[PDB]
Each structure stands twice: as structure tokens, then as C-alpha cells.
Length: 190
Image (cartoon, rainbow, N blue to C red; front, side, top):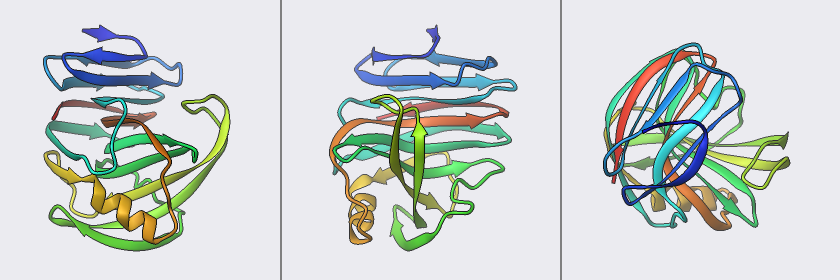
């Protein structure tokens, strides 16, 4: 069902849907691991399905239609605690590469594509534990796709080799993120 921001469980999967207060986003949970997000002139939002908590060796499958009209990402996305980290394995994006301006740390090949690795820092920003400063880890896929499998271990191991360690996992989902844009997406996670 179409819902406002919140977290919970639906048909066997964790979901998290968050936004910055701006309207324009229609997030809907569907059967199994399916969710859809249609947005018209949104602000910033992040929504999708997966697991709570995630694991450091999960092989995540996703498939669907991803039609961004501007700034948007399609990522395996999640958090850890101690250390507090917000991480992304970006499988597809719209008009803006999330690593723009970030210092590249390395490359890793996984599931049919090379990925470029980066670390960024969020200062005094919202997080799963409230206002906080924390690092973000990024693997950005060079060959964009809207369906496939992601062996998270390949990315977590590659990050670890660059000194990017993860704490105790919190949630782990496939998320559609948007930033003051429009678009449509329907994704099934497993």
C-alpha cells in the first residue's frame, strides 16, 4: 500500500521509506519483495525493501524498471553501527554521479562490472541514530543496470582493503533515492 515515510515489515521483507518533508513522492509496498516509487518534483527521498539486519555476505537480487528523470540512484543501501556508516553499492543512477567531487580510493570488479570506490563524510546530518557526523562508503557501478545480483561481500572486502570498515549491521535494502527530480521505478528484491 501507498504509505508515508516509516519503517516496518511487509510480506517477509523489511522496508524503509524516508524523505525530507517535500511532497511529490508516492511510495507503495507490493507483494513479496516488491515496491514502487513514482515521484513528481520531489525533494530528497530514499525508499526500498530488504532486511533488518543485513549481513556481510548477503547475495542480493533485484529486478525491475528504473526510469529516473534527473538526480536519482538505485543502490544496495544500508547502515552499520559502531562505526556508524551509511553505505551504497550503486547499480544505476540518473543525471548525477554520487561520487562527484569525492576522492577515488580504488576499483573492484564484481557481478559483471568494474566499480569505483569512494569515501565521503556527512557532517551534522540526519541518520538512523539522529543528528550525527559519519562516513559514507560508495561502490559505483560503471555498467548501469536495473536487474541483477550483488555479492555484497566483494564490496565490503574491497572497502576493508582501503581501510573502510563496517560495524554491526543495521538495515540493508535495495533503495531508490531521488533528489529534487522526477521519475518512476518498480523493483522486486530477493
